[PDB]
Every structure is written in C-alpha cells, then in structure tokens.
Image (cartoon, grey):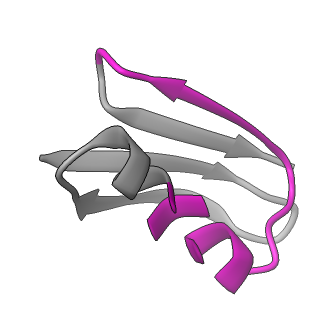
C-alpha cells in the first residue's frame, strides 16, 4: 500500500510517498529518508491515513 511522509524540517519541507507491505516497513524507508536529509525530530503515525509525520 501507499504510505506518506509529512516532512517539517528546518531547511527541508514537503511530502513523499512510498509503497510498502505494512506500517513497519514503511517506517524503516521513511525513518532512512529522514536520515538521508539530516532530519532529526519527533515522529507520529496515523494508521487510518497511513501517514507518517516527522517534525524538527
């Protein structure tokens, strides 16, 4: 299924999607995506919308 990441960093902001079999797999692309762009913050997830949010 399609999972989405709401990114709210200091220098980078936006939204990205990915295809994953479950939430766990989607978190571990999205929580590499954060690392990739030097984004370190607090995380939330919404199973109903399959949406991750990372905020710096």
Q: Residue furthest toward the left?
A: 1
- Picture quarter containing residue 13? bottom right
- Name above or below for residue 11 compared with residue 8: below
Judging depth in this view, the residue of 4 and 10 nearest the camera is: 4
Picture residue at 36% right of the left edge, 56% below the top: 25
Residue range in magenta is 28-48
In the image, is 4 to the left or to the right of 44?
left
Q: Position of residue 22 (x, y in %)?
A: 25, 43
Picture residue at 67% right of the left edge, 68% below the top: 34
In magenta segment, residue 33: yes
In the image, is 36 to the left or to the right of 18?
right
In magenta segment, residue 23: no
- Picture quarter containing residue 20? bottom left
Judging depth in this view, the residue of 21 and 34 nearest the camera is: 21
Q: Position of residue 51 (x, y in %)?
A: 40, 34
- Name above or below for residue 47 compared with residue 9: above
In the image, is 42 to the left or to the right of 31?
right
Q: Position of residue 55 (x, y in %)?
A: 77, 43
- Picture quarter containing residue 31? bottom right
């Amino acid at each position: 299924d399609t999972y989405k990441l709401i990114l709210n960093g200091k220098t980078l902001k936006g939204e990205t999607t990915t295809e994953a079999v479950d939430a766990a797999t989607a978190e571990k692309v999205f929580k590499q995506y954060a690392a990739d762009n030097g984004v370190d913050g607090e995380w939330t997830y919404d199973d109903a919308t399959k949406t991750f949010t990372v905020t710096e």
